[PDB]
Image (cartoon, helix red, strand yellow):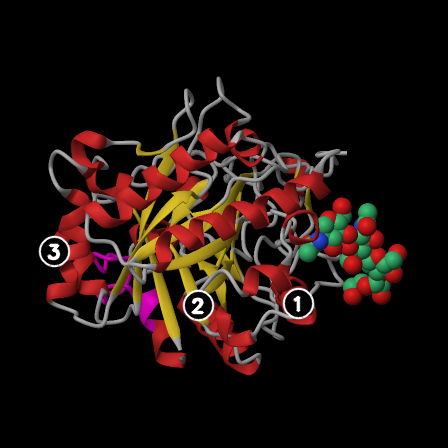
Amino acid sequence: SNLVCYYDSSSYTREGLGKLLNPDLEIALQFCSHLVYGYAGLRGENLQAYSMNENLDIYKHQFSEVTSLKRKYPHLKVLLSVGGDHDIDPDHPNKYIDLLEGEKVRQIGFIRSAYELVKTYGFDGLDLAYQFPKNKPRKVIVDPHAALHKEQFTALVRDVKDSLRADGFLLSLTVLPNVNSTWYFDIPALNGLVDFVNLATFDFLTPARNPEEADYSAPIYHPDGSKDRLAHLNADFQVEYWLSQGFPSNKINLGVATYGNAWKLTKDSGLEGVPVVPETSGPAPEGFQSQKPGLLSYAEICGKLSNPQNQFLKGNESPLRRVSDPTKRFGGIAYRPVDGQITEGIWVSYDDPDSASNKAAYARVKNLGGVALFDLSYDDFRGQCSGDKYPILRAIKYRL
Ligand SMILES: *[C@@H]1O[C@H](CO)[C@@H](O[C@@H]2O[C@H](CO)[C@@H](O[C@@H]3O[C@H](CO)[C@@H](O)[C@H](O[C@H]4O[C@H](CO)[C@@H](O)[C@H](O)[C@@H]4O)[C@@H]3O)[C@H](O)[C@H]2NC(C)=O)[C@H](O)[C@H]1NC(C)=O
């Protein structure tokens, strides 16, 4: 099976123990069949693909520091990903749709600039993690031209493929969280144009999108205990949609996340950690290592769960508790309510090594191509949790 390891290159410069330098990156490669360098973006002025940190990626060679790892792992394939929900540009918020709707000269400039990034820096191919409009989050028509945009995406993909053919470069698509495949992906047509598709079947709910209630963010199956939950928001619904639309199972990778979605609780959120958790208050305080409100790395979540340091501590120093449905269909929960001396309540939806292993077992049951892991920088690459480095990645590899 494949194990496609995403690498968010912003991790190279993080301040503190979330910093992922190249020796730690290399430790992962014994488990990964592919490494995907994230992320290039689109220029606001002309929609060309470009490095969002040229000083690092180009002038200090981080692109080729990563692609040259093929010298040490000769079968490793290294791709460059465009977009990924990491091209954040509030003053040019329409770039991805404008490229679809673009004049030929604008699209050709994107195709050529992408090609040149792949070739110049030693990549084996390109990942289009296209930043489509997402499902509208439900409180408590996004795109009137979706059908046109589907057709334009097929054509763009066809044109990107053509640019890659003579060199033999790979082309993948990533369907990002809450990107709706019915709206945008002509699945049977895309099958002839791309080598594989990663379905990012996680972050179905997040505190940024869903600040006032919390629910499982990456279940395999639909949780009937999640009152009123939208039925398409689960990994099996997404995978079965791609299979039923005609995509070969061996060309699909199941997306698994190494980070968790963390909500701030209130007293009114009550004492049940099984979701839906009501009356939440947006994102949890950022972790000191990951420094993103509402996200936590696996190491940060592990450090919050019971361990010999914190097991007897009280109030806001007490452990988060594990909530785990015995059927194992839905994923991990780390939880501490607002109660008593505890004033900082938190609910985290995440995969730990065991639930990530179960995602890999589901991939195998459905005869998928493998798993795509988002991303190495939030796996515990230093082994802070148990001493074992990359416990999530290894749990998935073990099962493939
Ligand atoms: C793209 O987004 C659209 C929404 O904008 C999404 O369409 C939604 O799909 C879900 C799943 O197919 C639909 O919900 C189902 O609706 C039927 C018909 O009313 C219900 O009977 C279903 O209830 C059954 O299944 C549940 C889980 O198995 C059970 O728990 C439940 O009791 C029933 O047994 C279920 O609610 C929803 O109607 C549409 N919405 C619209 C507006 O079309 C589409 O799936 C998204 N595409 C992708 C690929 O994600």
Q: Residues within 10 Å of mark 1 (few under 14, many from 20)?
A: some
Within the magenta stretch, is there residue 386? yes
Front residue (pair 300, 166): 166
- Cα gap from disc 2 to disc 1, whole angstroms: 17 Å
Give the numbered dot on residue 297: none
Rendering quarter of residue 146: top right
| Viewport quadrant of the N terminus | bottom left
Question: In the picture shown, does residue 311 fall above or below 116?
Answer: below
Q: Answer whether residue 306 is visible to the viewer in this image.
A: no
- The residue wearing badge 3 is 23
Question: Most prominent secondary structure in the magenta stretch?
Answer: loop
Q: Residue at 45% of width from left, 68% of height from top?
A: 356
Q: Is residue 400 left or right of residue 203?
A: left
- The residue wearing badge 2 is 371
Q: Residues within 10 Å of mark 3 (few under 14, many from 20)?
A: few
**Secondary structure beneath disc 3?**
helix
| Viewport quadrant of the C terminus | bottom left
- The residue wearing badge 1 is 221
Q: Residues within 10 Å of mark 2 (few under 14, many from 20)?
A: many
Say whether disc 2 or disc 3 marks the residue closer to the N-terminus. 3
Q: Residue at 52% of width from left, 55% of height from top?
A: 200
Q: Nearer the viewer, mark 2 or mark 1?
A: 2
Q: Is residue 123 left or right of residue 327?
A: left
Looking at the picture, how far across and down is residue 190, in whole percent?
A: 56, 59
Looking at the picture, how far across and down is residue 201, in whole percent?
A: 55, 58
Say whether disc 3 or disc 1 marks the residue closer to the N-terminus. 3
Q: Is residue 92 left or right of residue 79?
A: right
**Secondary structure beneath disc 1?**
loop
Q: Amino acid at mark 3?
A: Pro
Q: Quadrant of ligand 1?
A: bottom right
Which contiguous range is marked in magenta?
Answer: 379-394
Q: Amino acid at mark 2?
A: Val
